[PDB]
Amino acid sequence: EYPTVSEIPVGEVRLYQIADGVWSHIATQSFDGAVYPSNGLIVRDGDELLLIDTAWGAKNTAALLAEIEKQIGLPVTRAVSTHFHDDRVGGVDVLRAAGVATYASPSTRRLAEVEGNEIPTHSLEGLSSSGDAVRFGPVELFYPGAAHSTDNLVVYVPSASVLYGGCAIYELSRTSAGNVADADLAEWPTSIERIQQHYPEAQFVIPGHGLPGGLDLLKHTTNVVKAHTNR
Ligand SMILES: Nc1nc2ccc(Cn3ccnc3C(=O)O)cc2s1
Ligand SMILES: [Zn+2]
Ligand SMILES: [Zn+2]
């Protein structure tokens, strides 16, 4: 049963089996008066592991590495942050030290720099315009367009029909748009139309924060976004 934020002390990381050679990774961090949970993904890359997103923090990300050695036992060799916020890039410095080559789109790198966040080393190309798709080892990386922010990526594991939505996909229980500082509310529903065109098969869809679901999370996220602009 998927862990909730109440169950995960800040500084601990949990791993959850979505499908064979596919895990999400759940951690917790303080922010705007509370502590929030945050999701990333892990994919078996042959005899290696591909990570998607940090654990929101240096000490957390290092507890992620430790739980991955304890529980899987193969080496993380690459990581991909999916947009520029520290719940995606905080910890890259730790991953770097740990042997992991860290990647992000060219925008994602510049944005974080300005915002003072940590900076993935390598640049990912082919991802410049709404709807580009590129192949990263055992996954496909997809830029559906401006959404939670203007740089966010989504990830699809074809062999498992798992789609990792990141923060541009909300969980079902979330009904308040939230901090929409850097989002594009006008384009975000259209961005979610693309996802739904390019990944009609998805079996499970993993939000950036909270419980996984199906493709329902997409019409949910859209209803949540549009409600926010009519008031
Ligand atoms: N019911 C819920 N409400 C909220 C409100 C704000 C957030 C904010 N947040 C922090 C880090 N990333 C985000 C983000 O929005 O991606 C998440 C949830 S989950
Ligand atoms: Zn964000
Ligand atoms: Zn987030």
Image (spheres, rainbow, N blue to C red):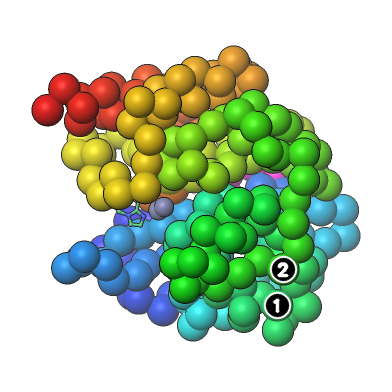
| Mark toward the start of the polypeptide (2 vs 1) | 1
The residue segment tinted magenta is 16-20
- 80 in magenta: no
Using the rendered image of the protein, determine whether residue 217 is visible from the camera's viewpoint: no
Relative side of 150 to 127, left or right: left
Which residue is more in the foreground, 130 or 169?
Answer: 130
Snapshot quadrant of residue 81: bottom right
Relative side of 11 to 228, left or right: right
Q: Could you tell me which residue is drawn at 63 percent across and 40 percent down?
A: 155
The numbered dot on residue 6 is: none
Using the rendered image of the protein, determine whether residue 185 is visible from the camera's viewpoint: yes
Q: Is residue 182 above or below residue 156?
A: below
Residue receiving disc 1: 96
**Marks 2 and 1 close (CB-CB < 8 Å):** yes
Residue 198 x %, y %: 64, 20
Which residue is more in the foreground, 162 or 70?
Answer: 162
Which residue is more in the foreground, 170 or 66?
Answer: 170
Q: Could you tell me which residue is drawn at 70 percent across and 30 percent down?
A: 132
Q: Disc 2 on helix, strand or loop?
A: loop
Residue 177 x %, y %: 24, 39
Q: In this rendering, which labeled residue sits more in front, label 2 or label 1?
A: 2
Mark 1 belongs to which amino acid? Arg
Real-space CA distance between mark 2 and mark 1, rounded to the nearest whole angstrom? 8 Å
Q: Residue furthest right?
A: 47
Mark 2 belongs to which amino acid? Thr
Q: Disc 1 on helix, strand or loop?
A: helix
Residue 183 x %, y %: 37, 41
The numbered dot on residue 121 is: 2
